[PDB]
Amino acid sequence: TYQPVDITTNTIPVTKEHYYRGLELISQGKTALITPAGGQGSRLGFEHPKGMFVLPFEIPKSIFQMTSERLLRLQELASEYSHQKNVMIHWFLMTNEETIEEINNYFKEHQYFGLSSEQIHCFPQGMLPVVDFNGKILYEKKDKPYMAPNGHGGLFKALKDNGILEFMNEKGIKYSVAHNVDNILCKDVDPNMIGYMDLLQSEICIKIVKKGFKEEKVGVLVKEQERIKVVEYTELTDELNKQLSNGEFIYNCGHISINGYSTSFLEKAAEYQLPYHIAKKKVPFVNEQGIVIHPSENNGIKKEIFFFDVFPLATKVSIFEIQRFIEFSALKNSLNESFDNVNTVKRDWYRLNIYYLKKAGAIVDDSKSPICEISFRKSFEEEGLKEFKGKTIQLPFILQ
């Protein structure tokens, strides 16, 4: 039956040796980033791909612009370490036939936020028609079905079919970090994580948060016949919710969708047949007397495949613990909910930036204001802030 999973970083610590090996691999052109453009930002006020959403900071920037600036800073750190003149991180962005032209135009007319046109690569995944309960296609108009992407599990076949695995081998790319578009604090191609997976020779490196309470809406890792799997929150049991006498959960590895993969593993994954799941949706339709109905409950069925069902294919897997305060704050809802919104993201980013200033030797006075904005182009962790050692800073503070 199911057995518990050990957190690798509890007994094999992340060290400075790992960080510098990561910078070396980035400098040699051996790394890449993989992300989705996102579904439509409709939960927000935004009828466009989620990456285009402008965060209302004191200096406003889109999600796509944040990611561009972090890649520029990572390239710079690797270049300063190795003394190598041109350092490049290639970025593969998964989209579909309906949205690919709009995303390409968005990057071109912003002159790629300072990246090169040679390093940005948009590619499409498969789509399927949405159906009703006799399995019959739901239509938008005559000869025009409603369509949906095949699920995030469609990543692996899409990389093969679009020639991206061939391109990785040509360029010498060995390790890729894949993550979701909603987490504003994500470290992207994290040198700490690249160095850790290389020295342990992992196929997959999975980032986790320690589970906080029984009803937390997060999936958890389990072991079955020596292979790793995810159990989704909706399928948890009394057995899988058991606690030790000290209050800690036996099954405490919360999966948060920041995962590293070797190129050889991606080649295996592309050939693997993933299991189908049912996901539901609200879809407008014409009723018995010709009226268009906008339903109050879900009425459409989307047939999907899930990327995490690939985990049990691997034989070499490492588990990397992160702190929520450092690398987890998601944007999911409008301000008509009190969680995962623009205000909760702001509060979390400001508190992290104060912490980094203090770690660099500064004294911070927050008595009048909470504002502390540090550009992703200027510092990755605290390393860009050395000029403030022994200095007294009174918020608001803005560094661009």
Image (cartoon, rainbow, N blue to C red):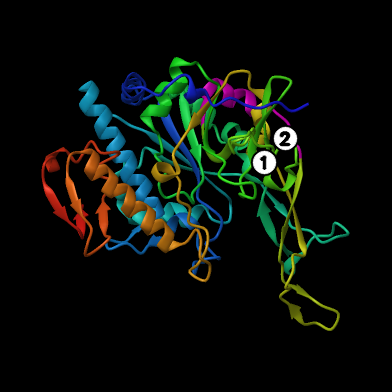
Give the image location of residue 371, x and y in percent: 26, 60
Q: Which residue is mark 2?
A: 274
Magenta span of residues: 260-275
Q: Amino acid at mark 1?
A: Phe
Q: Position of residue 121 (x, y in %)?
A: 45, 41
- CB-based contact (under 8 Å), mark 2 and mark 1: yes
Tell me which residue sits at (29%, 38%) in the image.
381
Residue 347's place in the image compared with 328, above or below, is below
198 in relation to 248, above or below:
above
| Residue at the limit of the structure toward the front, as seen here | 245
Say which label, 2 or 1, has the lower sequence index: 2
SS for dot 2:
loop
213 w.r.t. 140: above or below: above
Residue 85 seen in render: no
Most foreground residue, 233 or 175: 233
Q: Position of residue 225 (x, y in %)?
A: 74, 20
Q: Classify 10 Å Cα crowding around label 2: few (below 14), some (14-19), many (20 and above).
A: some
Query: Residue, x 75% and y 66% (percent of image)?
Result: 139
Q: Which residue is mark 1?
A: 306
Q: Secondary structure at mark 1?
A: loop
Mark 1 Cα within 10 Å, few/some/many (few <14, many 20+)? Answer: some
Quadrant of res 130: bottom right
Name the side, left or right, on which 216 lies relative to 259.
right
